[PDB]
Amino acid sequence: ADTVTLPFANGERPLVMYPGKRPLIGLTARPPQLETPFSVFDEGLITPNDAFFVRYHLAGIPLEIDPDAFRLEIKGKVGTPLSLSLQDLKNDFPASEVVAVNQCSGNSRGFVEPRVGGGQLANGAMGNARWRGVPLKAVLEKAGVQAGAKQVTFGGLDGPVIPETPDFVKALSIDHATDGEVMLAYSMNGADLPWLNGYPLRLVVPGYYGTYWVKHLNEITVIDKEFDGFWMKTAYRIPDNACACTEPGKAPTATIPINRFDVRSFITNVENGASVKAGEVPLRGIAFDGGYGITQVSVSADAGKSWTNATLDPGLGKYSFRGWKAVLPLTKGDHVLMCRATNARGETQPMQATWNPAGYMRNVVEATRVIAA
Amino acid sequence: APLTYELPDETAQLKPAPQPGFEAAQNNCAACHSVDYINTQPPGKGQAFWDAEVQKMIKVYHAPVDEADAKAIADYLAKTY
Ligand code: HEC
Ligand code: MSS
């Protein structure tokens, strides 16, 4: 009818219908937070615009935009401040395109044990799309970045209902901002950005968690110091260690901002309790990382006692979902299926889930029980 | 003309309780965001979790909530959710 239950405690959610969107999993209404049903990820490598997940922090989201009047301001430690129209971006600068995953820092938080506070998401706070726009490098070079620059800040049209609440503003290092891959995207899957995905312009930060991907982006500031805004200084912090993790119940001793994705993979064509025919069972799914390249996906039908190599689909780019397929002989009875990806720098997925106070960065080997008959 | 976007109606509500914190939460906890933020938190988290949530809203986000109301709200939440 109109609700679903996610597979964790207090998992009931309304199915909600927004303009331009198919029915999605409603987390919050004001501001909107919308999760993608898992089944969508079995429909193809690129997430359709009408299915793409939505995450916002502040209730004052823009609800009327005049695209002709819209301006992107570039200011701070630059030789020439710029005020750029959408027409300017499309006409005066080379276009670039990238197929890239956007995934929220807190994707899968609902599965973290012990449970932690925050957005109680299943795995649907991620999506893959073909972004087109201008490399930020090109716009910054036009402004003329000055020696001594350290960071670039990014702010959008949304704001707090109460002005004392800190504005949503994020920062990137200057070397990252000018790397050529960070993009001012005006197009998503060949169309103008859906409204809730940041119409008319957003930052795309390939291989970095979604918090950086500032939507409705209208203000870019080059600064000669580290940005100390709340959403960099206090929010979006991970343990400053290799595992980005702590002992359950324990605060980190030091933290750093969240940054690149860790390696993830999913089986998309089966879910818990699915029936399959005993014999050769066809499996398929996706894998992704921070852009180093998926080297392999191993698949198991006996809870990781033994692994079979999956065949990797032809790729769409190092920042995209990477498809994979495997055919496994399954004897009659119950089987715990797992998949596990590794990337070209040797990052992989832990067999046992780790923990951090914020519930960011989950990437445990996913297990799915099926019934072969 | 500009382009515009229409949101569906908000319907999220707090779980009624006889504790006075129910009305104080209705009066203080929907000013910035819908109460589905609260309704969807992990269940039976208890007193320390909800004490911390309320204090964060006040200290970090500047929710204008006085001390008596803050305790009423956290107590109602810990007992109800
Ligand atoms: C504006 C000053 C707020 C008031 C009034 C209240 N809260 Fe709030 N809350 C605010 C922000 C900026 C956020 C983060 C939004 C995001 O999407 O990240 C929240 C979030 C919450 C949550 C989710 C958990 C968390 O982020 O800590 C909960 C459970 C929550 N808020 C509860 C809550 C209660 C009980 C309030 C009455 C005291 C309340 N909020 C008021 C800002 C504001
Ligand atoms: N402007 C803005 N932007 C922005 C925001 C907000 O809030 N605001 N959010 C973030 C986040 S945080 Mo976590 O890390 S995820 C995320 C993302 C999402 O996207 P979409 O919604 O499009 O999907 O976004 C990004 N951007």
Image (cartoon, coloured by chain):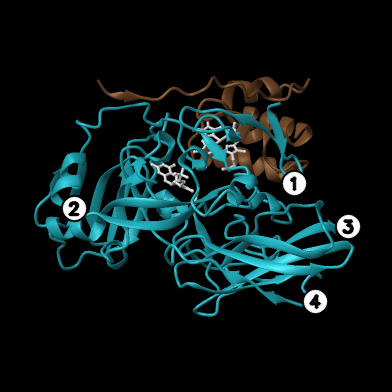
Chain colours: A cyan, B brown
Instruction: Looking at the picture, tell me which residue is in the foreground, A357 or A10.
Output: A10
Chain of the residue that carries numbered disc 1 in the rendered image? A
Cα separation, mark 4 vs mark 1, equals 25 Å
Residue type, mark 3 in image: Ala
| Residue under numbered circle 3 | A373
Q: Quadrant of the N terminus of chain A?
A: top right
Return the disc, 2 or 4, that comes first in the chain's sequence.
2
Cα separation, mark 1 vs mark 2, equals 47 Å
Looking at the rendered structure, whether the residues under marks 3 and 1 are on a common chain is answered as yes
Looking at the rendered structure, whether the residues under marks 2 and 4 are on a common chain is answered as yes
Return the disc, 1 or 2, that comes first in the chain's sequence.
1
Cα separation, mark 3 vs mark 2, equals 66 Å
Find numbered disc 2 in the image and state the secondary structure of the residue it sits on.
strand
Residue A118 appears left or right of A195: right
Instruction: Tell me if I can see residue A307 in this picture.
Output: yes
Q: Quadrant of the C terminus of chain A?
A: bottom right
Return the disc, 3 or 2, that comes first in the chain's sequence.
2
Total numbered badges shown on the rendered structure = 4
Instruction: Tell me if I can see residue A121 in this picture.
Output: no
The picture quadrant for ligand 2 comes to top left
| Residue under numbered circle 2 | A76
Looking at the rendered structure, whether the residues under marks 3 and 4 are on a common chain is answered as yes
Find numbered disc 3 in the image and state the secondary structure of the residue it sits on.
loop
Q: Where is residue A88 in the image (x, y as percent from the top left)?
A: 15, 44
Find numbered disc 1 in the image and state the secondary structure of the residue it sits on.
loop
Chain of the residue that carries numbered disc 4 in the rendered image? A
Looking at the rendered structure, whether the residues under marks 1 and 2 are on a common chain is answered as yes
Residue type, mark 2 in image: Gly
Return the disc, 4 or 1, that comes first in the chain's sequence.
1
